[PDB]
Image (cartoon, rainbow over all chains, first blue to last red; front, side, top):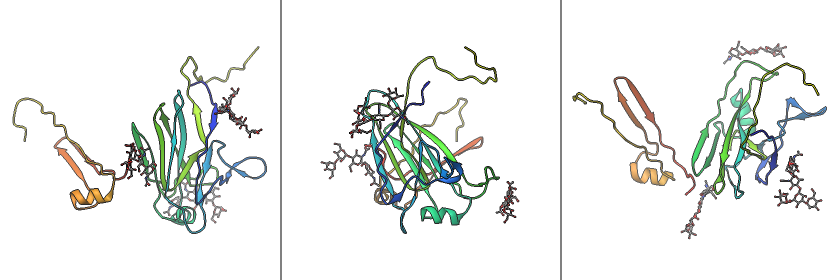
Length: 162
Length: 54
Ligand SMILES: *[C@@H]1O[C@H](CO[C@H]2O[C@@H](C)[C@@H](O)[C@@H](O)[C@@H]2O)[C@@H](O[C@@H]2O[C@H](CO)[C@@H](O[C@@H]3O[C@H](CO[C@H]4O[C@H](CO)[C@@H](O)[C@H](O)[C@@H]4O)[C@@H](O)[C@H](O[C@H]4O[C@H](CO)[C@@H](O)[C@H](O)[C@@H]4O)[C@@H]3O)[C@H](O)[C@H]2NC(C)=O)[C@H](O)[C@H]1NC(C)=O
Ligand SMILES: *[C@@H]1O[C@H](CO)[C@@H](O[C@@H]2O[C@H](CO)[C@@H](O[C@@H]3O[C@H](CO)[C@@H](O)[C@H](O[C@H]4O[C@H](CO)[C@@H](O)[C@H](O)[C@@H]4O)[C@@H]3O)[C@H](O)[C@H]2NC(C)=O)[C@H](O)[C@H]1NC(C)=O
Ligand SMILES: *[C@@H]1O[C@H](CO)[C@@H](O[C@@H]2O[C@H](CO)[C@@H](O[C@@H]3O[C@H](CO)[C@@H](O)[C@H](O[C@H]4O[C@H](CO)[C@@H](O)[C@H](O)[C@@H]4O)[C@@H]3O)[C@H](O)[C@H]2NC(C)=O)[C@H](O)[C@H]1NC(C)=O
């Protein structure tokens, strides 16, 4: 693609807290999170079933980056999302993905046994993005513009010069 | 059984209802299952209820 250009969209998440950060990702002195990801926790006693739709009406492809949260315990899972088994379903006209989070521990890193699985979805012009979840969703704040062209990546330690 | 001297290609499918009421209205039990196996392999698909865009 050769670009990180991010377009922030208007996703409206109701009955659910946004912006939730952690100690393992820090911005400034306080807690923080992935800048392009929105971590949603419950509000009150309830985390509602979320059904939302984001149409792509533009003439270019959209790349949405999202995630799924894996708690290291049932007490964390339920403490955050209410229902003890979460679900995330991301579908367009041409495809769908359904991920059901893995509770339990995988070996510690950065002080946490809980992780995130990252997934991407491409939305073509005239197609809509649809997002549906009962819990365990790290939502997109928008998309990345997709370009076609000569850009690439290379692994090197060589210094750069003028 | 395939008793012939040539390979057979079987095409089949799984039905995804847009509702539990359609699923149960059609198939009785609210969670369906399909398992297709030969000696050398197997596939097991459990249908996705719910809506994908019209
Ligand atoms: C990453 O880049 C995004 C896209 O912009 C650009 O990309 C970069 C790399 C460069 O190439 C730039 O030259 C290029 O423009 C940034 O998104 C931008 O964010 C700003 C600030 O929030 C948005 O400004 C607002 O635009 C509103 C509508 O604009 C219309 O036209 C644009 C431009 O083509 C379209 O994208 C839109 O869809 C609209 O059709 C406008 O109404 C707003 O005015 C109101 O708000 C201001 C306060 O911000 C207020 O003063 C005023 O009274 C109004 O109430 C506002 O101007 C801008 O739309 C948006 N650009 C795009 C292309 O989406 C993004 O910020 C950047 N990321 C970071 C973190 O820097
Ligand atoms: C299945 O087995 C695995 C391995 O035994 C287990 O996961 C492991 O959990 C332990 C802790 O229970 C992890 O060890 C950590 O190491 C860090 C780094 O130094 C420590 O800081 C951690 O200890 C903290 O908490 C302790 C208890 O209060 C304090 O004594 C300590 O000072 C710290 O505050 C912690 O011990 C270990 O890293 C993982 N295993 C792996 C391979 O990473 C898991 O819990 C077991 N699951 C079940 C179902 O029992
Ligand atoms: C999660 O959200 C999605 C999107 O909101 C939703 O799926 C959508 O269902 C609507 C209808 O409920 C679909 O829109 C259809 O568009 C056709 C084509 O023109 C209409 O003909 C359909 O309307 C018929 O039925 C209506 C109700 O009686 C009548 O008013 C109308 O005249 C027609 O008879 C229908 O509105 C839409 O296409 C999908 N979404 C997408 C992206 O395709 C889904 O139901 C939501 N799920 C949950 C759990 O709530």
